[PDB]
Image (cartoon, rainbow, N blue to C red):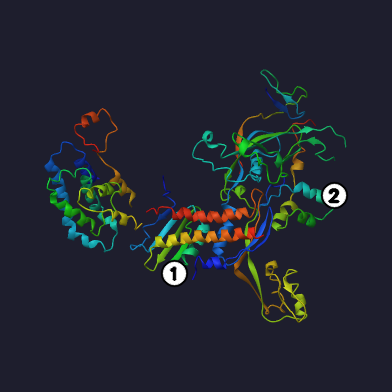
Amino acid sequence: EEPDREKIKLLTQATSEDGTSASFQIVEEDHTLGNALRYVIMKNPDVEFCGYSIPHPSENLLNIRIQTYGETTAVDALQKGLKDLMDLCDVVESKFTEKIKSM
Amino acid sequence: EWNVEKFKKDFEVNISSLDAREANFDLINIDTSIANAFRRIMISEVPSVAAEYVYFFNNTSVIQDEVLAHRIGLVPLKVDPDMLTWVDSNLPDDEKFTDENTIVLSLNVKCTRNPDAPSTDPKELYNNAHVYARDLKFEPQGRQSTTFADCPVVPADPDILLAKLRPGQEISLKAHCILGIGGDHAKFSPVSTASYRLLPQINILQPIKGESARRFQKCFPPGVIGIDEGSDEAYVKDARKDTVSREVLRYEEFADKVKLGRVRNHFIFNVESAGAMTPEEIFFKSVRILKNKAEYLKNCPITQ
Amino acid sequence: MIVPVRCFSCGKVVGDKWESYLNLLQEDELDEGTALSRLGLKRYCCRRMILTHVDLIEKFLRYNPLEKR
Amino acid sequence: TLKYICAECSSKLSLSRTDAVRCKDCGHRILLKARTKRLVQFEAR
Amino acid sequence: KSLQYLGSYIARAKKLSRTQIIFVASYLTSWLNRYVIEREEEVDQRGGMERFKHFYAAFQALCYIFCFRHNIFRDTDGNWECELDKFFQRMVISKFNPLKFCNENVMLMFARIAQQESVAYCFSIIENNNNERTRQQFIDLQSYFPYDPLFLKNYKILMKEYYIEWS
């Protein structure tokens, strides 16, 4: 097959040598994914710094930055916040399925 | 502190009403960034079917060709999506429109003078004077004859006045209706207004029983504040009923005894539709897009 | 020209309510306030699309160059 | 099938070689060109 | 690009003598152990791994020979020339980590061979190195091979006498 290799992109000019302070660049995204993903990364007790940034509104690029206190990289913290964003959309989908049954 | 099992305990949905067109429900104990993400996907990401390419053979009416094409694309079609797949605009037009992608609609109208005696109404005076959106006839190109035979393609609002004619004039076109999202163009947006309001909170501080209780009724919508006497004095019955008019702060009698605030986690969504899908189903489709918007990043190589 | 298909601000389909609105005012003899509220228009962005429409296509269709006189 | 239209009587009209530019029913000099079934395409936007 | 032309020339050449194969790799191992104190102390210093692209190429040219000419260095007794059975696994455990920064094919082609030919074991390190996860001009100078087989057909007939295929 062929995994898509232009969507997520780690910017090595802003990336730490340990791996714990990195900045990613996602194409074709906006505040929708970025503000929802930042909420979920910031609930990790090991995350020190997290915020997103849209550089210019005319192109559809999303920079997010994660900094951790050590003992977890910014890629291990990005993928916990991608897991819990999936598992949060599976609680909203289940409570709303039951109440349609419960009418 | 936050957990994905503590979110499951505190999150609740209260569906207020539901219809074939609109759906009012609640989201208790969810974040403003998550609730805004569901709002955006219903407007800008849930796909719909709309006329993208319009092919005029003749148009001898008054309405211009590029205006009359634009009015066809804004018609909501009652196609169920995922019966179509997505078009591919990197390969040419002879390869691009297969019947798995495209729904073909056509229009053939000619206006003639009607023999009638009487100022008189122009539908008792001409033939095919007004062109409605139900004159877009579905042409099942290919294998669409058997899979769109339970549900034919027809506009959700058939009485959309598309054009008007006079005798001599004609409109003869054929449109190609394709699948797309509403961040491309506003015609592929499935929803009239998918939007939330945040739950109002009316914090009484001092008791306002007596004459104060009668005019503090009239600072709010007629079912919000309740009164009995000095006994069972003044309280909120339904804060969801309250429009936030701030009409009680313009009176110096009550500008100290109440703090209007919001419950910052209780959202009140009002999802509507154009008519293609049901508004409880453009919310399941929206909560699953954000799920798949993060599966696509978890299962992706971190380049460079 | 003709009534717009959709409202500009919200996106409700509004194009099917122009010939309905003219018969509400002519035959039922309603005011403009109740006749807009009967048609399911209740956002002021969406009220003014039917409320404040000119419909100049009736003046443009008087000039038919295909029909004699 | 050749088709023009006269601007006065709206009588549809053909115009060959060595003709006057006049209508045949009326005597009108201004005479406008009709449109036929021919393909034009539009992005409905 | 010059080291890239070195390893592909020694490997894909039928008429090269047995002493000339090793004498390239003798000098190619002489460059890599003179490197052992002169620049191996600079790894935890400041400056990323782009500083050692000359080292990351000359190691790869030596590992390109072991993928194609392992069977000239060895006698029946097994005595490897310049002690390759000591050399590779001492350079793999170096601070530069030369199994992560070289080409994905030729360093894995080295991994399925140095286990069999009993020189160095590295399937627990390439397993390790890809689990941690400017450059595109350096990937593609490693991917390029000067002496790949020929798209021309009447000229390869001459080259059949001169050129070593895959096996």
Q: Label 2 crowding class (10 Å Cα cut-off): few <14, some 14-19, many 20+? A: few
* Residue B204 image point, x, y percent: 67, 78
Quadrant of the image occupied by residue E69: top left
Q: Please say whether residue B54 is visible from this viewpoint.
A: no
The CA span between labels 2 and 1 is 69 Å
Residue at x 28%, y 57% (from the top left corner): E49
* Residue B112 image point, x, y percent: 77, 32
Circle 1 sits in a helix, a strand or a loop, which is it?
loop
Quadrant where the N terminus of chain C is found in the figure: top right
Residue matched to label 2 = C27
Q: Please say whether residue C51 is visible from this viewpoint.
A: yes
Residue at x 50%, y 69% (from the top left corner): B2
Q: Nearer the viewer, mark 2 or mark 1?
A: 1
Answer whether labels 2 and 1 touch (C-beta < 8 Å).
Answer: no
Quadrant of the image occupied by residue B196: bottom right
For the residue pair B222 and E70, the one nearer the viewer reads as E70
Q: Which residue extends farthest right? A: B118
Q: Is residue B111 left or right of residue E107?
A: right
Residue matched to label 1 = A45
Circle 2 sits in a helix, a strand or a loop, which is it?
loop
Vertical placement of residue B198 versus B126, above or below: below
Residue at x 72%, y 57% (from the top left corner): C42
* Residue B93 image point, x, y percent: 53, 35
Q: Amino acid at mark 2?
A: Glu
Vertical placement of residue B226 versus C56, above or below: below
* Residue A70 image point, x, y percent: 37, 67
Q: Amino acid at mark 1?
A: Pro
Instruction: Pinpoint the chain carrying mark 2.
Output: C
Q: Is residue E40 left or right of residue B273?
A: left
| Tag 2 and tag 1 share a subunit | no
Q: Is residue B230 left or right of residue B260?
A: right
Quadrant of the image occupied by residue B128: top right
